[PDB]
Amino acid sequence: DADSSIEKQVALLKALYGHGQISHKRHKTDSFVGLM
Image 1 (tube, rainbow, N blue to C red):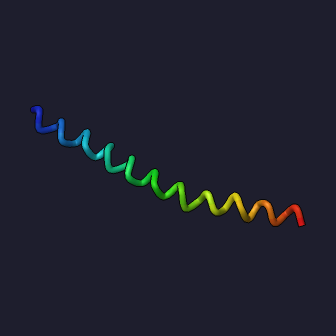
Image 2: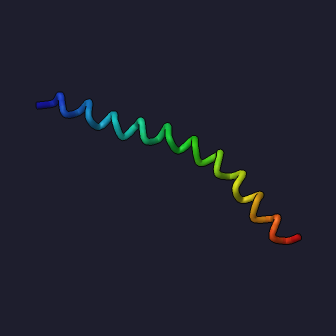
Image 3: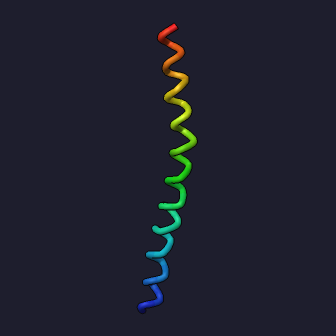
């Protein structure tokens, strides 16, 4: 029944996706174009 403990690791994979947020940080730079 502890085998379900491995399913919790799937949540750790979601933390790896958070690295994609760094790519969205470039979208904030596009917002500065509005200053023009």
